[PDB]
Image 1 (tube, rainbow, N blue to C red):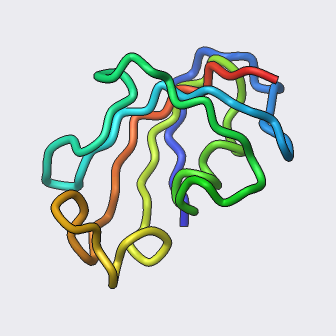
Image 2: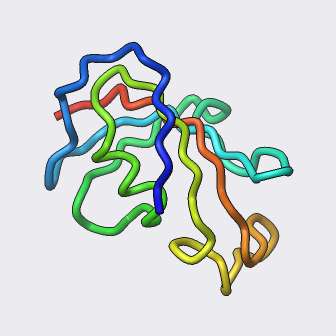
Length: 107
């Protein structure tokens, strides 16, 4: 499950396709928790491609459902990224992840 709450401005048509290296100013967040990962803090806006399962399924499905300029807001389920596993020190198991995703992409 990927719950999208798009803040309106964008274009609504430049969708990420397969093998398109796309750029996201992401900003991570835990439900009832703080940030854990931010491309805005690094100022390195995470040039990633679609179709290789580089990113988690909660972040991959939210990218193709957005367009250029759009500012959505992910609500990632635990079972798609780290629900039983959990990352050591960053993501606990059974965490419902929150992301500030703005698709200002390339290709």
